[PDB]
Amino acid sequence: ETLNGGITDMLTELANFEKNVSQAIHKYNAYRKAASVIAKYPHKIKSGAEAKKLPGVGTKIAEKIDEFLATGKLRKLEKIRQDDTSSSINFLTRVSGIGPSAARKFVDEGIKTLEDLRKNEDKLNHHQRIGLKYFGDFEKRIPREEMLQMQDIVLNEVKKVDSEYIATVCGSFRRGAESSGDMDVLLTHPSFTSESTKQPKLLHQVVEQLQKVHFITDTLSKGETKFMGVCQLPSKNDEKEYPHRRIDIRLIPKDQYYCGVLYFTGSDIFNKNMRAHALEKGFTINEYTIRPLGVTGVAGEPLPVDSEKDIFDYIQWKYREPKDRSE
DNA sequence: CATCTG
DNA sequence: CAGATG
Ligand code: NA
Ligand code: NA
Image 1 (cartoon, rainbow, N blue to C red):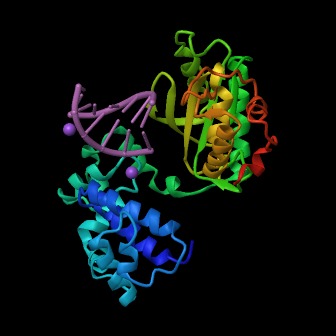
Image 2 (spheres, rainbow, N blue to C red):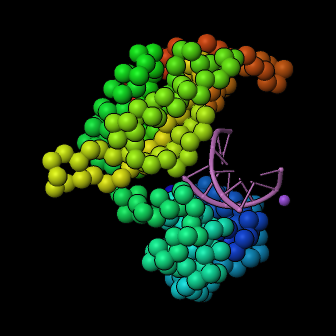
């Protein structure tokens, strides 16, 4: 956790690079287990060979651990940190809509910057365009104080359109968090579930309303159950308009809301633990359900949940207020 | 995983 | 349809 930190960090730099710049998924994947293992490892790696000793740790990585331990730096790390081509990719990629794949094409075309991008708005698709238009707003965190305002709107409009809707803002926002990156509203309706054959309107109706009042400003992606967009808190009395924020709305069958809700609320670590406890308690859990573990090996059949309560109970556990869902 | 592009 | 992105 700090005893093999540099090592783990270098490895991660290396890993990421393989993947984003080269196309070295193997290699890339290679740095990863290595960091994962040395990461677990209980002592102070004092040398290459010592590390080599681990699994996932081979000759090459050892070599590197050597140089790093031997001197505060890595040549290769140093070479990549410079190289423009590499730096560009780390950069273009910052744009919502640009993954590595795209980042490579652009660079090989010479677009290596924001301006480049602008000059070539023609080569970018809808998503990417919005992403470019809001580069700035997109990187700005969302102060909870804003979140509450947003949340107030979404919730009210959903209400108007149908009393039967059930919306919830998952995220860290949910677990307390003073600010967040984006807004995800989990959504369900009684008239929508596991069997129930579809109801696209269910999601389209609300999205619409949201734009009707102007909360939503752009559409990144709109499918039958998942909407990806852009919203904004109405600029009060002209002098201070808000940044544009990322937002997601997802339809969930009412019969798998809470697991979902639970799930998305996190944290990752809270999940896992609750996840492992479940198991002990003779249970299975995932994104949509909680199942009674048979003994033959495994086994299923969806336990019936009405709240986040029904779940905990199941695995017989202390109901956790969202704030305490930390670890 | 669900969406989009081409 | 494979393949990218989030
Ligand atoms: Na991106
Ligand atoms: Na292939």
